[PDB]
RNA sequence: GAGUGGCGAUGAUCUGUACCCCGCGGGGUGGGUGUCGAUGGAAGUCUGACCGGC
RNA sequence: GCCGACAGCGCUCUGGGGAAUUCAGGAGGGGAAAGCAGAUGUGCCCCGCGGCGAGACUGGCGCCGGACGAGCUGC
């Protein structure tokens, strides 16, 4: 069910790096429930999930509402890599990252979901 | 120079001779747009050579599910052997207009003397066909009975369900409306059963003292009839009803032996046994709904039932509408639908969320995962119980 | 604000089949419920009887680009009770339910979606309503559902694609009438994320225009969305119904 | 509507034969007044927008009965060199305009084939026939009529063209398979009647190929036995019947159709000492078959239908007639 | 009966075979069909209980007030009995009151608000004020209410065609009075020729 | 020398169902509830002599 | 909510309204196979031009081309 699977040749790495930079700019909603709140409230600019979920059904619900809100989603293959990409000390299973009016981070979100649009 | 073309529609194939062909250089001209806009001019361009309906909606569903990927069927090759002339590409060919490129290549592959202009390539047959799609209601009305839009609608539900595998794993229906009717008829049997207790109890007082459990009252006042003709152990029933020897039956025949109230008549007793058969058949149907409802819910979404029980899991699935909606809600939104009480309210709300989306988005979901969810519930109950 | 049980009267909107419900401290755009007693995705709705029957689902510009355009001040929406609408990019059938509430029982909505899961919720909603057809196919392949869609009056377009004008281009070249309605939602961040949004909007208008539409008006959806445009145009004629 | 214009072409096209009928002594002048006015009323009715196949057949019936009226009145007044071909050409025009406007009307198509057959227009009949088959390919009426008239004309290859394309198309009902076994065995009846033809494995191929079809059932196989059960004067009818009964008793061996052909199987090549002989042989198969564990009600209804299905024959033992009446009473 | 011709007249059951053919039937299992089928037999059991309850109330009201039954019927008269509570407490009320039984919200709205009082109450669904139309509705509502105070007063203060000796006379007078009200000529109008002469 | 047990994004914690009277225990009214009641209340049961035909 | 002077402004004038009908136009919707691009009776045989087409030879460089032809059919 991971048909937007991100490729380990550095697209995963740019995803997790932009996760970390958004974590340092506090633009980051972590975990599946808070990701779901950000997508349902429409604050979300991009959303990554983790395909290393042991039952992946517990994150399969957010591609629905991301298709409804028309925000790009993409899966990285490790919730541990996403977890310390956030800086959490636990495994983050699905992360959402928003934006503001003016930031270089918002530019990096723009180019990043341009690459996600090249996937989907 | 297009000779024939092929219009494939949700009721069947139909291939048209075209004579007085289109202005292949002046297609974007406004008067040609008018002649491609009204029926009384374009119909001078198109005839109707053949129509081929669908002998069954199964043939329709295989017809979509071949023509979407772009493969012709053996009956389409049949109708084209029927209609097209026997041609190689030796000395005289036949141009056919086809709305699909791979169907064109397969159809020139099967028939060597047809040559097919596809409406993705050439705007001549794209327009000459686009206008058969505009007027193909009136163009087909003389031979196809009934509307085309319903055959389209059913064929689109059929192709969406056959492509997505919809109702093989969508069984939400049988518990939302089922808990609606279950709580509804529980209210009804409380109402009417309280009525028959009020009125036969108006005839015969102390049966309210010996026998509670309203539906067992209703069956025992179906069987006891009148105040007159009593024996305690009459026929094969009261041992299966309740206690017999020391407790109830002597209070029944003794209570009517020392009875106190008003007498009643026969047609009134017909009201109390028609109303009694009302209440006890309502209770039997309640047993049927709880049995098949709990079995079905443990066969469809077991996680909410093991962590909650099928009446309140039924109340949440009817309360949010479907497994897809309740799965789409977050944790605290399910928490919409001292601090220890609200704290464990938040914890069971969160596990009911995780149980909801694990309950829906498996194919035919299992049972032990909700079992280990209730194992976490028991060890958090123990996590407070260390106090 | 718009609490459950507040008295709020309903008057018609300027468009055909669109309603506006004015209350004491607020107003709420709303459509008429085609299947009464049932909310699709859990929305507030309005019940009233003739002087049981009449019901009005409240329609959200934050969950619907078309409600964002109607509250955005759009001249026409091309859709009326009786229309045929080709909806593009139909996730879960929510705005497809509001369009189906506009065109009503005698209308027909032809919902197209690529994803199977929104396909499933679309088959739930489209099993409840009988004027919407479910089509789960690729919008980049209109010859897949050329056996399913007749010549429609309106095309609504909400896809998050970089080749959006090409997709709507070939879909209109197969299914949209002579002088047809087209109503496209555009996300400038989705087409070109490194360009300014007015330039992305004007370039998409130019791609429709050399795709032989005729742009009537453009409005940007910006008290309700950011960097979203709604372009209202008409296929092969300057004036709509022909 | 420009019905006065196009109607004006058809009326002015009709005029010189009315000229010749006025100048011959055949019709009189007020008769031609009624005739021109009624031609006109039909032409405006027919070229009118909202029309019906009933209306087209009304004007065909009236125009053709006009041609017969002028024919008999011509034979009264002993005229010759007046001809019918403007009437026949005109009637082909009414039909061509008819099945151009309402082409999904098998009343129009069968009536136009009837006219084209009654005026001895054979090649044109085949052209109309092919156009009718192309607009109604799921019509066993048309495929049967094309195959049968092709067979009676004598071109069995063209008959088999119409039939094998027919069995390709009409595959819901068994009807056209029954008529192609019926017409192919009609041809084998012609071949053995004139005496490949010695083997005749073609309707056996129709049978064994017909196994794999969506209609293929036991009652339909009993209709195959009703088809093959006639023309018992042949070479290999026992081989064909025997293959049908053998194959049904290899694929559906527990059905009262198979027990019914187990009864009626020795009565194929009969029509006479063998008639009570094979009749009592059918009493051995009958008493052997009615006791068999199967759909006993269906076999009982089939044998009420069959014992009733013999009664019109003469020259029979009245004890056998009465005891089959008592067997109908007993079942 | 579906999942033949006794339940419903034919050629509509041809339509239910037609919609049974071409409909959008989602093939649910026979267990769920057993649940919806047992709800069907539940509600047709309640329809049979409606039939015999209706015959119960008809025969019982014939035994309690035959004057009422031989004016307006068991259901409407039973609802008058149910409003005022009992037979003697229905009999203690005047004929205008028995006209306005069932319309007390509009009635005290009108009387406290200086407006038009309601013409009838429960009475409207009898077999007679429904038979009339126009001003005959309020008029026969009045006189039916007067005759029915009289008849229920006879039943409440004392084979069945001598016990029902008031209701038959009030039926004959009140239905004859009906047809003399309804079958009336219009207002006399002059006829004018082609020239207005 | 071997085999068990161990929080947290698969969601920790915090403002918030009220106030008050007492030694984690108890009590006076909450407000929203969901029931069946109830006799209790809003709450009292139209007008009254002509009209139609001719 | 009716009435409303003076001053000022606008529309209109065989004064201003309402209804009935007769006549003259205009705009829009919906319905309609809504289809007179070349309008020659039918059938057979002989010729002429051509199409399918089994089967058969050949030239030049793995192809392309020539030129034979049972039969069947169109016009």
Image: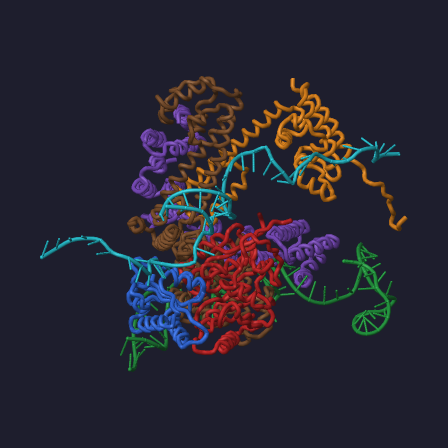
Chain colours: A blue, B brown, C red, D purple, E orange, F cyan, G green
Number of numbered callouts drawn: 0
Residue C239: give x, y in percent of width and height: 60, 70
Residue nearest the observer in this picture, D111 or A40: A40
User: Residue visible at 56% across and 60% down?
Assistant: C29
- Visible in this render: residue C108? no
Is D136 situated left or right of D235 in this image? right
- Visible in this render: residue D77? yes
Residue nearest the observer in this picture, G41 or C122: C122
Residue nearest the observer in this picture, D167 or B363: B363
- Image quarter for residue D288? top left
Q: Is residue G3 above or below residue D251?
A: below
Residue nearest the observer in this picture, F38 or B38: F38
Q: Is residue B42 above or below residue D195?
A: below
Residue D120: give x, y in percent of width and height: 54, 54
Task: Please identify the residue farthest to the right as the structure is shown.
Answer: E197
Residue D150: give x, y in percent of width and height: 45, 52
Q: Is residue C233 above or below residue B278?
A: below
Residue D172: give x, y in percent of width and height: 43, 48
């Amino acid at each position: 069910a991971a048909w937007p699977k991100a490729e380990d040749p550095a697209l995963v790495q740019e995803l997790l790096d932009c996760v970390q930079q958004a974590s340092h700019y506090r633009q980051l909603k972590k975990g599946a429930n808070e990701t779901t709140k950000s997508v349902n409230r429409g604050t979300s600019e991009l959303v990554i999930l983790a395909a290393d979920t042991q039952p992946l059904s517990i994150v399969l619900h957010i591609p629905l509402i991301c298709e409804e809100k028309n925000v790009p989603y993409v899966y990285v293959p490790s919730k541990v890599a996403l977890g310390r990409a956030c800086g959490v000390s636990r495994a983050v299973i699905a992360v959402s990252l928003t934006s503001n009016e003016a930031s270089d981070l918002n530019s990096k979100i723009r180019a990043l979901r341009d690459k996600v649009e090249r996937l989907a | 120079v297009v000779n024939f073309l092929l219009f494939e529609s949700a009721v069947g194939f139909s291939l048209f001779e075209v004579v007085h062909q289109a202005d292949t250089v002046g297609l974007e001209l406004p008067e040609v747009k008018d002649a491609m806009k009204t029926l009384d001019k374009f119909g001078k361009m198109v005839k109707l050579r053949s129509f081929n309906p669908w002998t069954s909606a199964a043939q329709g569903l295989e017809a979509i599910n071949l023509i979407s990927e772009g493969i012709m069927p053996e009956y389409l090759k049949s109708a084209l052997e029927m209609n097209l002339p026997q041609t190689s590409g030796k000395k005289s060919k036949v141009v056919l207009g086809v709305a699909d490129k791979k169907l064109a290549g397969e159809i020139t592959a099967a028939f060597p003397g047809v040559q097919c202009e596809a409406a993705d390539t050439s705007e001549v047959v794209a327009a000459l066909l686009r206008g058969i799609r505009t007027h193909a209601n009136k163009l087909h009305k003389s031979l196809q009975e009934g509307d085309i839009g319903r055959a389209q609608l059913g064929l689109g539900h059929a192709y969406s369900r056959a492509k997505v595998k919809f109702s093989v794993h969508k069984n939400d229906n049988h518990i939302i409306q089922g808990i609606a009717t279950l709580d509804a008829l529980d209210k009804s049997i409380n109402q009417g059963a309280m009525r028959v207790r009020e009125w036969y109890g108006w005839h015969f007082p102390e049966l309210i003292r010996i026998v509670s459990d309203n539906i067992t009252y209703a069956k025992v006042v179906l069987a006891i009839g009148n105040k007159s003709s009593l024996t305690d152990e009459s026929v094969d029933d009261l041992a299966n009803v309740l206690n017999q020897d020391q407790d109830k039956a002597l209070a029944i025949i003794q209570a009517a032996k020392v009875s106190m109230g008003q007498d009643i008549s026969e047609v009134d007793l017909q009201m109390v046994r028609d109303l009694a058969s009302n209440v006890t058949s309502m209770a039997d149907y309640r047993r049927i709904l709880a049995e098949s409802l709990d079995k079905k819910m443990s066969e469809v979404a077991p996680n909410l039932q093991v962590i909650l029980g099928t009446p309140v899991a039924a109340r949440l699935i009817a309360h949010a509408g479907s497994l897809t909606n309740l799965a789409k809600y977050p944790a605290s939104t399910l928490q919409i639908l001292p601090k220890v009480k609200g704290r464990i309210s938040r914890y069971l709300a969160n596990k009911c969320s995780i149980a909801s989306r694990i309950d829906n988005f498996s194919e035919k979901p299992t049972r032990h995962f909700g079992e280990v969810l209730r194992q976490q519930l028991e060890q958090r109950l123990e996590w407070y119980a260390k106090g | 604000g718009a609490k459950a049980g507040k008295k709020v009267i309903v008057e018609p909107h300027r468009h055909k089949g669109v309603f506006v419900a004015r209350g004491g401290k607020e107003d709420l755009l709303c459509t008429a419920n085609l299947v009464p007693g049932e909310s699709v995705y859990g929305e507030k709705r309005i019940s009233v009887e003739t002087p049981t029957k009449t019901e009005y689902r409240i329609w959200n510009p934050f969950r619907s680009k078309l409600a964002a355009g109607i509250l955005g001040g759009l001249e026409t929406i091309y859709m009326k009770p009786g229309s045929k609408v080709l909806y593009l990019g139909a996730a879960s059938g929510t705005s497809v339910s509001h369009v189906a509430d506009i065109v009503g029982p005698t209308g027909a909505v032809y919902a197209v979606e690529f994803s199977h899961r929104s396909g499933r919720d679309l088959i739930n909603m489209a099993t409840r309503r009988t004027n919407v057809i479910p089509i789960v196919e690729d919008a980049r392949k209109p010859m897949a559902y050329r056996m399913l869609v007749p010549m429609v009056d309106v095309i609504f377009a909400d896809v998050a694609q970089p080749d959006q004008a090409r997709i709507v281009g070939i879909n209109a070249r197969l299914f949209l009438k002579q002088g047809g309605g087209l109503l496209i939602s555009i996300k400038a961040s989705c087409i070109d994320s490194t360009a300014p949004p007015e330039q992305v909007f004007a370039s998409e208008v130019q791609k429709l225009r050399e795709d032989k539409f005729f742009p009537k008006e453009q409005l940007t959806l910006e008290p309700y969305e950011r960097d979203h445009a709604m372009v209202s145009c008409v296929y092969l004629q300057k004036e709509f119904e022909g | 509507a420009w019905v006065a214009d196009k109607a004006r072409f058809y009326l002015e096209r009709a005029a010189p034969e009315l000229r010749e009928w006025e100048e011959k002594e055949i019709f009189t002048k007020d008769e031609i007044r009624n005739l021109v006015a009624k031609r006109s009323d039909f032409e405006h009715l027919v070229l009118a927008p909202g029309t019906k196949p009933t209306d087209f057949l009304n004007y065909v019936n009236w125009e053709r009965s006009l041609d017969r009226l002028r024919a008999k009145r011509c034979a009264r007044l002993n005229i010759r060199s007046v001809t019918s071909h403007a009437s026949q050409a005109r009637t082909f025009g009414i039909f061509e305009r008819a099945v151009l406007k309402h082409p999904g009307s098998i009343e129009l198509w069968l009536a136009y084939l009837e006219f084209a057959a009654q005026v001895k227009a054979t090649k044109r009949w085949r052209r109309i026939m092919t156009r009718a088959l192309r607009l109604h390919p799921m019509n066993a009426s048309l495929w049967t009529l094309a195959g049968r008239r092709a067979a009676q004309n004598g071109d069995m290859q063209r008959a088999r063209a119409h039939f094998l394309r027919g069995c390709r198309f009409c595959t819901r009902e068994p009807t056209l398979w029954l008529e192609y076994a019926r017409c192919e065995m009609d041809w084998l009846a012609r071949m053995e009647a004139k005496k490949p033809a010695l083997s005749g494995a073609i309707p056996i191929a129709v049978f064994d190929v017909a196994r794999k079809q969506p209609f293929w059932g036991p009652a339909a196989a009993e209709k195959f036995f009703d088809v093959f059960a006639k023309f018992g004067h042949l070479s290999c009818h026992e081989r064909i019947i025997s293959h049908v009964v053998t194959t049904m008793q290899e694929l559906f061996p527990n059905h009262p159709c198979t027990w019914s052909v187990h009864i009626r199987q020795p009565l194929v090549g009969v029509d006479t000492p063998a008639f009570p002989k094979a009749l009592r042989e059918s009493l051995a198969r009958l008493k052997a078959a009615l006791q068999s564990t199967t759909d006993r009600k269906a076999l009982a209804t089939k044998m009420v239908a069959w014992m009733d299905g013999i009664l019109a024959i003469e020259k029979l033992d009245a004890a056998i007639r009465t005891v089959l009446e008592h067997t109908k009473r007993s079942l | 009966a579906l999942g033949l011709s006794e339940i419903l007249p034919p050629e509509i059951e041809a339509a239910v075979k037609a919609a049974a053919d071409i409909s959008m039937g989602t093939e649910i299992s026979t267990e769920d069909y057993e649940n919806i089928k047992l709800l069907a037999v539940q509600v047709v059991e309640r329809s049979e209980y409606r039939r015999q309850l209706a015959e119960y109330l008809q025969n019982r009201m014939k035994a309690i007030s035959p004057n009422m039954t031989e004016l307006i019927g068991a259901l409407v008269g039973a609802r008058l009995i149910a409003h005022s509570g009992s037979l003697v407490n229905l009999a203690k009320n005047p004929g205008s009151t028995i006209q306005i039984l069932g319309a007390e919200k509009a009635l005290f709205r009108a009387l406290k608000t200086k407006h038009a009082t309601p013409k009838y109450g429960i009475i409207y669904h009898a077999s007679l004020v429904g038979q009339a139309s126009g001003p005959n509705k309020g008029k026969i509502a009045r006189q039916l209410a007067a005759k029915i105070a009289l008849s229920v007063r006879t039943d409440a203060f004392e084979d069945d065609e001598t016990r029902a000796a008031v209701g038959i006379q009030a039926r004959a007078k009140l239905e004859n009075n009906l047809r003399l009200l309804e079958g009336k000529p219009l207002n006399k109008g002059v006829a004018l020729g082609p020239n207005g002469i």
